[PDB]
Image (cartoon, rainbow over all chains, first blue to last red; front, side, top):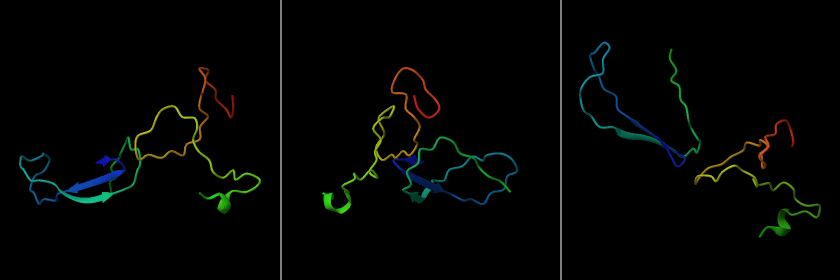
Length: 49
Length: 49
């Protein structure tokens, strides 16, 4: 999230066993990192190995 | 006041500001782009118009 110069990073890691699909389940997202940066952001890309 | 600290008799021209801009800004935002703003209805490119 990016609100008012503030970049919010929320996370959850889970061990699973599934090959392709998105499972049905429920677990909340704890906040992890706030960054007081201040950029206007319009696009984003992920990066692989 | 900072009159005796930085103001020179030749005119301290290091203190710049954005006077012309297309729109009002959101809170907590900064801008450093220096493109020539079409203050009139004619478009203008290059370095001046």
